[PDB]
Image 1 (spheres, rainbow, N blue to C red):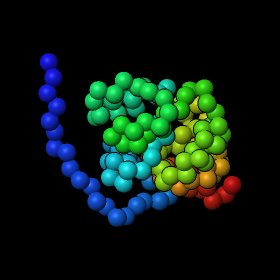
Image 2: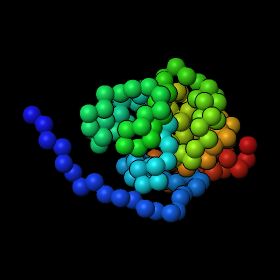
Image 3: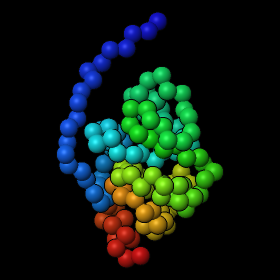
Length: 143
């Protein structure tokens, strides 16, 4: 059985956020939707996917630039952090994401942050702790 009606709504925020923040996932999906900003995601992290694909029904994982509610970019477990960054160079869109090559691909916060300066596109970053926005910003300042 099927029926799909919901409160669709129009975001109109002229503004935009920069730097790292201490958001999580739903906060991010809101701002992403709001601004139509681009969201790099890794299908590897099924925990993230089990939220997205449920918030944006009927989707059944894809690869590539996933226009599905939010503008996503689905890059593999197998593509290195410098390679996905090189790809994102062509797009050069304002992003909002978590520190990408931090945990799915086995890094540390430092190694993540360094690699992320090599991204030549704007990117709001979200760490799952406030006390780490400081640390992460610190790497972005110090390397």
